[PDB]
Length: 365
Ligand SMILES: Cc1cc2nc3c(=O)[nH]c(=O)nc-3n(C[C@H](O)[C@H](O)[C@H](O)COP(=O)(O)O)c2cc1C
Ligand SMILES: O=C(O)c1ccccc1/C=N/Nc1nc(-c2ccccc2Cl)cs1
Ligand SMILES: O=C(O)c1cc(=O)[nH]c(=O)[nH]1
Image (tube, rainbow, N blue to C red):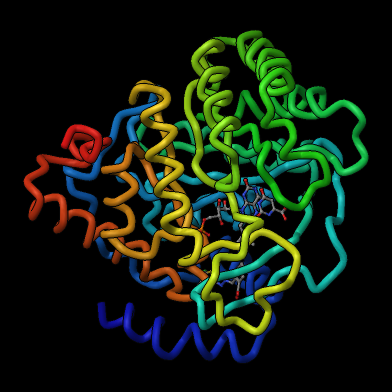
């Protein structure tokens, strides 16, 4: 809490004053991968443990995809106190992504806009990187610290479904869960994969590839969706997810909308907006998807989480787990312990025995 204030009031503002967002991100990835991190002294209580997706998670707060795109900082991220880590998005072939600058801070809105465009080291490099620590991950997982791998598609690929299938085959055996990302705002055509007939075709192929993996190397498969879907889109996704037995949903990616009230000078930059202005749009999408799937499909809630309250609202709305990313760029590593500490306090105040009891509680009021 002393370092929470120091990081929040002094350290982070100073690094932000010195470095553009992409440079700061690269540096943060480097520091994290080296273990150069403050004391994550928070000890996870049993209340925070969640069992879902065929796994135990010792706390429900994860790092969202996009921070460790290439699988370089996984262990440093667990050391930061995250109960699970998602790397990616990873595309089959290496690709540079969009021209710089492609990441923008909106300090007045506690928001970020990015158009990275799936910069990726590619499947082969990430595979070897994960292979080098595969058995350490197997122990982490057994210990309640699972690993997710988020799959993207190359900019120039003609068959999107084959890009994902390739990802399932190459990184599936190294992952506790896979994410089919059909919601990036920064790849042309990508989000139209969210439509019904095309999503059914895509996910059928994905699940078939997954089912062809040997039993101990067979990950759960989740779909990550946008916060900008029509009601029709959401109904169709819920329907396809139930028809195919998709294991879970990640809700949500960044928004292409610009909510009224944004103050940041850079608010009109092209890209996906994350952070505080996304928070409630995201929570509302979780609420809708939970109801449409009858509370039977696990949801990882993400978008604008920076406190225990933010996390609990998404849990009560139907999320079994939450992720954050943008909060980390403003508050630094201490925000992880902060969210966990506040979440636990709020669960007790509201009469929940643990996180599990709170999941979807709003729908039973
Ligand atoms: C700079 C940046 C890069 C991101 N890259 C990815 C990505 O590659 N794949 C993905 O599924 N989501 C990506 N995201 C989205 C996050 O995973 C998350 O869905 C979104 O930022 C909302 O969470 P937040 O408000 O806590 O940041 C990225 C977000 C940011 C800010
Ligand atoms: O600066 C931005 O606007 C930005 C934008 C997008 C993605 C990452 C960042 C930067 N994030 N900076 C981070 N710093 C840390 C950090 C800060 C202090 C000590 C150790 C670490 Cl790992 C974690 S994330
Ligand atoms: O690589 C990107 O730019 C990116 C991917 C994604 O899924 N979400 C996002 O906000 N940006």
